[PDB]
Amino acid sequence: VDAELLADGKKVFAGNCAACHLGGNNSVLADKTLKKDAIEKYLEGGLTLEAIKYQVNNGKGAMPAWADRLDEDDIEAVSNYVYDQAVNSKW
Ligand code: HEM
Image (cartoon, rainbow, N blue to C red):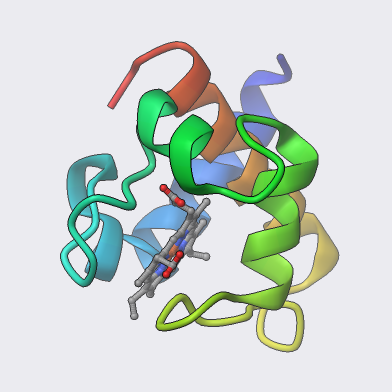
């Protein structure tokens, strides 16, 4: 996986997502974390980059939609960061 893509995604995550997903968890709805088993259980589409990106773009519930707030490169990077963190158990 491109190291600069992940680094970019980490930065986007710190700036925009860690407020509700510190540590890969979820301070708003505790079960629906960014960890692999939670994503597999709760995210529509399961643990895929497409699924992650879809929810980052379009929101869900109290998860804000970001497609009108972040550019496509930031959305791609943060989705790849979250996927990498989850699939590789890096949180
Ligand atoms: C920052 C751009 C950001 C990302 C990235 C992100 C990702 C994300 C995913 C992938 C999920 C699904 C997790 C699951 O187990 O199902 C998810 C879910 C929720 N999020 Fe989020 N999220 C980002 C930002 C934020 C912010 C700033 C908040 C709080 C204001 C937030 C909240 C939540 C909530 C609530 C959920 C659960 C949605 C649901 O199914 O009800 N996210 N996020």
